[PDB]
Image (cartoon, rainbow, N blue to C red):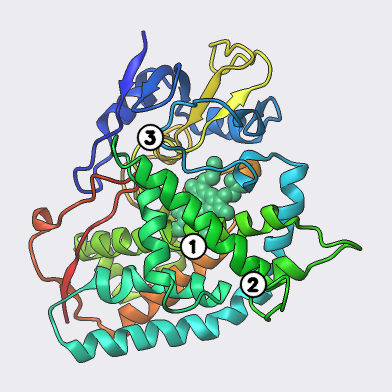
Amino acid sequence: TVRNCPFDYAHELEFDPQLRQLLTEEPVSRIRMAYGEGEAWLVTRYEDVRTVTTDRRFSRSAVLGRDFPRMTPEPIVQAESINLMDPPASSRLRGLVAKSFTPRRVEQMRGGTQRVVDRLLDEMEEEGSPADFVARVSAPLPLITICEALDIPEADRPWLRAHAMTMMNVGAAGKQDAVRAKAELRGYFQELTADRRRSPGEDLISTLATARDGDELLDDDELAVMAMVLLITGQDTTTYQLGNIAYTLLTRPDLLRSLRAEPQRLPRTLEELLRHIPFRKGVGIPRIALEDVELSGVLIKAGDVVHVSYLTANRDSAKFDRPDELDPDRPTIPHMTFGWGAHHCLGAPLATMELEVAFSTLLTRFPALRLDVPPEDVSWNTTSIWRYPLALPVTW
Ligand code: HEM
């Protein structure tokens, strides 16, 4: 009755078979995952999952305090984080960083992102073919950008990601690691944010720390946590989707030619890769059903833990015809790669912009770009809630 879900599948970017089976055959299923007390529902259908993310009957505020079935021994979340608030209390702090990424603002920052990318490739060319696209592009760019954004000193950055990542370990014994790593992170911002509030720079932490509706909207905890949360998120998913997309383009010659034939297809192609590419293992933060809510003919009692799978949502044949096929031409329908509902991804805008400025430069600069080894020789991360390539040797 209750499925085992270690969610350990890692083979290339192949869609987790357990997930494909639960989509087609038990689109609402009882499950139990690596760590946490109790069990939880798993909703896998587009429309059903859309329901769960938006319908005020399901709270993420209600998760505060539960040993919720999750994939990391220590939960990645914190108390005062945007992740454990719903609208309305979310909408005020979301509201504030959302100013920072209006298309005017993000289509300004482009300028600098173009100069970062250019320099990163002006360096990879200098060290000469072959090279690691992960080391020389996919890893640095997202980290530079979010640090530039937050005015993070150059010396702290390699440190800060090697803590960000440590919190994303699914490893039983890397839990003390995680709780210390997390608290050291909290602390560093606790201070460096209280150092902006104090002598506001003209960066983004300053934008958060200085905004005042009469009396500063953000409390110090509320801020330090928001500056800490913006750093973590600004440098995992994006670094990974830069490797994932690269791999996919260098292993689907038809796709990669089509783009080289008509580069204008790129913003449409990226959406379709985004949809497809299963850019994580398992399921992230759940929600609690606040009241009984039947959902695909299955009552969910009040106080039950609900997970949604964004990855099965994207591959729902009810929404996308030939869903497993990767058609950048297909009738555009909103993907759920960037989340949905209240907690939809806050940095969608900026990762959009990084992915556009990256692959559009790559494509022109290195038309000849090819994977330098066979695809099955590429090693895929196993230790993370995310899926990404460890290295991506390329020629040009
Ligand atoms: C390809 C790039 C990215 C992907 C695929 C991605 C994906 C996601 C996803 C799937 C969620 C799901 C939250 C949920 O539904 O429960 C999320 C939340 C979030 N992402 Fe991202 N993200 C990306 C880039 C970024 C960037 C650059 C930032 C930069 C600040 C960012 C900040 C956030 C934040 C703050 C949340 C939490 C919002 C909330 O729960 O209220 N993301 N992201």
Q: Which residue is mark 2?
A: 204
The label shown at residue 159 is: none
Labels in figure, total: 3
Quadrant of residue 226 within the rendered picture: bottom right
Identify the mark nearer the N-term, 1 or 2.
Answer: 2
Say which of 196 and 253 sits in front.
196
Residue 211 shown left or right of residue 301 in the figure: right
Say which residue appears at 61% left-offset and 17% top-offset: 303
Question: Gap in Å between the C-alphas at discs 3 and 1?
Answer: 23 Å
Camera-side residue of 42 and 383: 383
Q: Is residue 55 above or below residue 273?
A: above
Q: CA distance from mark 1 to mark 2?
A: 13 Å
Q: Quadrant of residue 223?
A: bottom right
- Can residue 333 be seen here? The reply is no
Q: Which residue is mark 1?
A: 234
Q: Position of residue 141 (x, y in %)?
A: 39, 74
- Give the class, few, some or many, for how many residues have Cα within 10 Å of label 1's Cα (few <14, many ≥20): many
Q: Is mark 1 within 8 Å of ligand 1?
A: yes
Q: Amino acid at mark 1?
A: Gly
Left or right position of 157 against 82: left
What residue is drawn where x is 54% and y is 55%? 186
Label 3: which secondary element: loop
Indicate which disc, 3 or 2, sits on the residue closer to the N terminus.
3
Residue 396 coordinates in the image, percent (x, y): 17, 82
Q: Measure the alpha-carbon separation of dots 3 and 2.
A: 32 Å
Residue 69: quarter of image: top left
Locate residue 59, reporting x and y percent: 65, 30
**In what element is the residue under mark 1?**
loop
Amino acid type, residue under disc 2 in the picture: Leu
